Image (cartoon, rainbow over all chains, first blue to last red; front, side, top):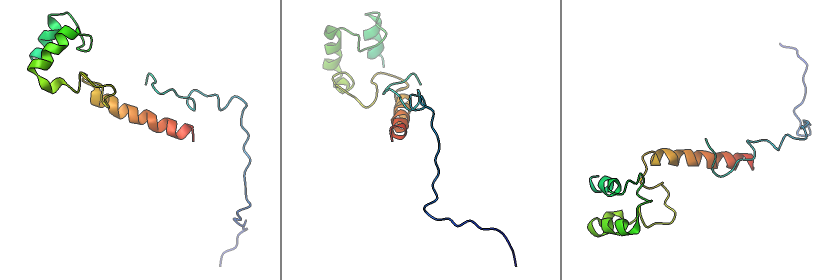
Length: 37
Length: 71
C-alpha cells in the first residue's frame, strides 16, 4: 500500500498574480520594428 | 567584380547606391544583370551588402519577438 494526502485537480483551481503598475511599460514588450540589436 | 569597384573608385564613393545616375546607367548598358539590385523598391535582402544574409536572419528574429510580446 501507500498513504498520502491528496488535493483534487479541478478546473476551478485558478491563480491570481499581482502586477506592478509600470510592468507593461517595459522596453521589451514595446519593441520598434528596427532595433539596434 | 572589376566594374563595380572601379565605377565607385573613379567617383570616390563607398556605396554604389550613392553613385550618380549618369554613372549608374552606364553599368546597366554593359551589364544587364544589375537591374534588380539597382532598380527595385523593397528588396527582401539589402542590396550590395556583405552581411545581407546575416541581416536577414536577424530580421526574422525580431519579427518573432514582437509576435510574442504583443500577443
